[PDB]
Image (cartoon, rainbow, N blue to C red; front, side, top):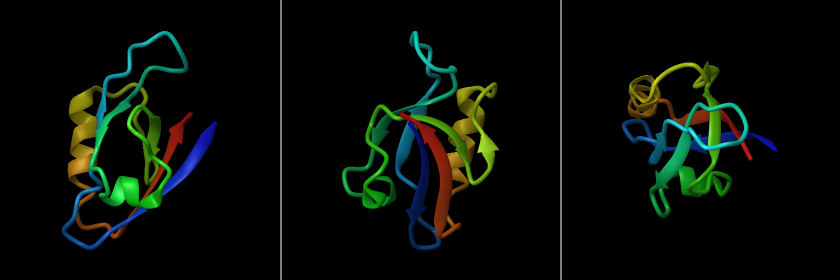
Length: 89
């Protein structure tokens, strides 16, 4: 279940999602929203719910890249105003 997650926030604010190197036995390993601000941008959209296997952010495929890359993407999503990240359900 692909999901065009759109996380809108104020410039200078991070999405609020914490994904980890998904290594379970399902889908293509990439990332796992292990955590997510209870009410933050991620929860605001009402789409991403801790445990979502994100696939890409604003056109940035998280597949094949380690956690360091993904984290940097989330951290760099502070002053975007919105996040077009397609996750996997």
